[PDB]
Image (cartoon, rainbow, N blue to C red; front, side, top):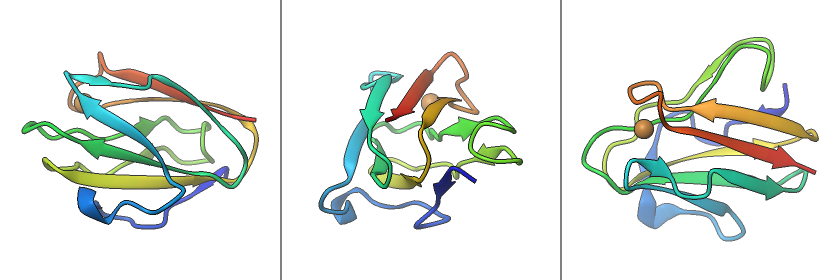
Length: 105
Ligand SMILES: [Cu+]
């Protein structure tokens, strides 16, 4: 695999780690839709909206299986720690017009 999951389920926005890089989910978009990070960085998405949102990487992107992130309620967060260089596309399962990518250098 190319990422580890610190918390399998969402956690409170106010619990976000120091050093995490944050991507806000607001205005029905990933507000940083192309994020560039380094190997070993933790990316945290935060849902600012009432509707649930997640991040979803299809099979073969972060590893063999799809990574279907948990549904984040309003003011919840979810993190992934990227361990290998690559370009990792994702989308929102309930709202698949929402697209993003993490580029790990
Ligand atoms: Cu979404």
